[PDB]
Amino acid sequence: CDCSSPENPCCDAATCKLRPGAQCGEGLCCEQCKFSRAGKICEIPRGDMPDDRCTGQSADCPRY
């Protein structure tokens, strides 16, 4: 499923998959059914490492 609730307007409830025009249904890098812009910070480490940032081509916050 792209969406795990039937109430999510990004998917069709009947299919649980994205509607035409939607790039995503949930995830830290999904913004109103579109991919969040590339470089948007999505995870800030406790240690002295660079932030994870949205790639602009995935709904999830990458690990790297």
Image (cartoon, rainbow, N blue to C red):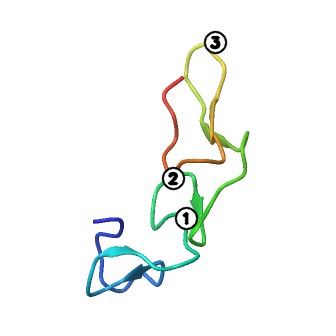
Provide the residue designation for mark 3: 48
Q: Quadrant of the N terminus?
A: bottom left
What type is the residue that disc 1 sits on?
Gln
Counting residues from the start of the chain, the first of labels 3 and 2 encountered is 3
Q: Nearer the viewer, mark 1 or mark 2?
A: 1
Residue visible at 66% across and 55% down in the picture: 36
**Dot 1 alpha-carbon crowd within 10 angstroms: few under 14, some 14 to 19, many 20 or more:** many
Residue toward you, 17 or 26: 17
What type is the residue that disc 2 sits on?
Ala
Residue toward you, 12 or 36: 12
Q: Residue furthest top?
A: 48
Relative to residue 28, is residue 40 drawn left or right?
A: right
Provide the residue designation for mark 1: 23
- Residue 24 at x, y = what percent? 50, 64
Residue toward you, 54 or 14: 14
Residue toward you, 43 or 20: 20
Q: Secondary structure at mark 2?
A: loop
Circles 1 and 2: CB distance less than 8 Å?
yes
- Residue 62 at x, y = what percent? 51, 34
What type is the residue that disc 3 sits on?
Asp
Q: Nearer the viewer, mark 1 or mark 3?
A: 1
- Residue 39 at x, y = what percent? 73, 39
Residue 31 found in image quarter:
bottom right
Q: Secondary structure at mark 3?
A: loop
Which of the labelled discs sits on residue 59, or is there none?
2
How far apart marks 1 and 2 lie (CA) works out to 8 Å
Relative to residue 28, is residue 38 drawn left or right?
A: right
How far apart marks 3 and 2 lie (CA) works out to 25 Å
